[PDB]
């Protein structure tokens, strides 16, 4: 079901992450981390302290889909085991995946983001914040990922 998911998404903040390649998203999925440019790092750190959940929604450029979404579990940190991104980067955020399944853009055509001029939510620069109701509904469109137990994620928050 979707009830724990809705609980996790309650009063969350949402950010679009655009990746130039699948290899980086695959790495993020395996390793539970993300790194972004300083401008977005600052926004994410601010958002992590401000909200019960901060959700990253991932899209690989030119793929025509979202590849999943994850919750920030920490602020960014520096000096750790170097991640071999296929690329100046900020620190590393730990993340917990909520959904590692794909969603085609064809399925989110009805969702517009008030924070990017009410353009379809698929449209946006890396780090674009997604407004609460748009973001919530977007996460709810994804196929449920039955490999993830959200109890574990709830126990952080």
Image (spheres, rainbow, N blue to C red):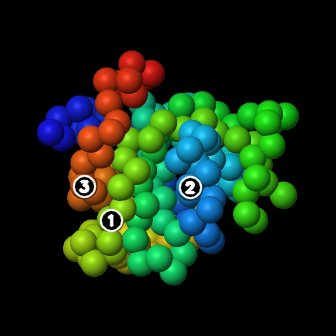
Q: Which mark is residue 103?
A: 1
Q: Residue 153: percent from the left, percent from the top?
A: 39, 28
Q: Name the residue: 31% across, 24% down.
A: 151
Q: Name the residue: 40% across, 50% down.
A: 100
Q: Name the residue: 73% across, 63% down.
A: 86
| Depicted 149 relative to depicted 105: above or below | above
Please tell me how crowded label 3 is: few (under 14), some (14-19), or many (20+) other residues with Cα within 10 Å. few
Q: Nearer the viewer, residue 41 or 83?
A: 83
**Would you name the residue on which mark 3 appears?**
143
Q: Residue 66: percent from the left, percent from the top?
A: 41, 65
Q: Nearer the viewer, residue 30 or 75?
A: 30
Is residue 137 in sight in this rendering?
A: no
Q: Nearer the viewer, mark 3 or mark 2?
A: 2
* Residue at the far top in the pictured view: 155
Q: Which mark is residue 26?
A: 2
User: Of callouts 3 and 2, which one flags the residue occurring earlier in the amino acid sequence?
Assistant: 2
Kindly state the secondary structure of the residue where label 2 is placed. helix
User: Of callouts 1 and 3, which one flags the residue occurring earlier in the amino acid sequence?
Assistant: 1
Spatial separation of the CA atoms under disc 2 and disc 1: 16 Å
87 displayed left or right of 57: right
38 displayed left or right of 26: right
């Amino acid at each position: 079901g979707t009830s724990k998911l809705k609980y996790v998404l309650q009063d969350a903040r949402f950010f679009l992450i655009k990746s130039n390649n699948h290899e980086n998203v695959s790495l993020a999925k395996a390793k539970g981390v993300w790194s972004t440019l300083p401008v977005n790092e600052k926004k994410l750190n601010l958002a992590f302290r401000s909200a019960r959940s901060v959700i990253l929604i991932f899209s690989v450029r030119e793929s025509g889909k979202f590849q999943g979404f994850a919750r920030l579990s920490s602020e960014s940190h520096h000096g750790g085991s170097p991640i071999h991104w296929v690329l100046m980067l900020g620190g590393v955020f730990k993340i917990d995946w909520i959904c590692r399944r794909e969603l085609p853009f064809t399925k989110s055509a009805h969702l517009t983001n008030p924070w990017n001029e009410h353009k379809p939510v698929k449209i946006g620069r890396d780090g674009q914040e997604i407004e609460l109701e748009c973001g919530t509904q977007l996460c709810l469109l994804f196929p449920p990922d039955e490999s993830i137990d959200l109890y574990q994620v709830i126990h952080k928050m």
